[PDB]
Image 1 (cartoon, rainbow over the protein chains, first blue to last red):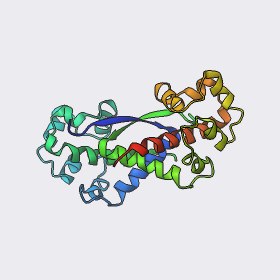
Image 2: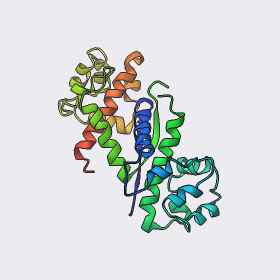
Image 3: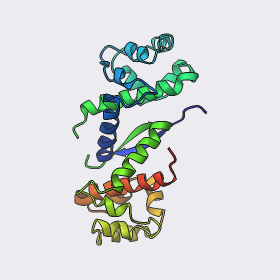
Length: 117
Length: 117
């Protein structure tokens, strides 16, 4: 289609292993394709404005505003409830991949902070 | 929870990265809790006996036989269809976590075999 998502089954032990693994990848810059270093620098408490800015999504952010996504937890919640939030709100498909890539790393970091290990 | 399953959403690119990541961990010995190092050496074509032997599950294997699970692919396929296979057959809960840990890591390796990047 473009960028399909697959729901994998993650057991409690493997779950924390994967979540923390990707969190480290997102925390410490290791991606040149997508600036994750700035993404992990963003506090999810501000919203998603900085997240969009990180990928230069100054116009795509409007889609979030339309859906009521401009707060903390909402973006993650929408991801857990749907995951295809960006596709649903009307995000540009030409950059859909880049958006979803950064979004995934963000979720991992967020969960890793709550991860008991 | 012990070894409960949580649905995680994996992006196409992240999916292969995660699948291969766990396969690497389960391949090269890095755990003392679960003998995954020998598990990655096990041919899932012999059945599940070798897998049970790895963790010294010479008694729990009976539960599999009871359910009719003693063939190749059957255990993994049953995991896909049920996921609570070991729980259903009557695996000992005191070792249930370890069984599932090796089980999950094994599936990751198996899938990684067909996994490109």
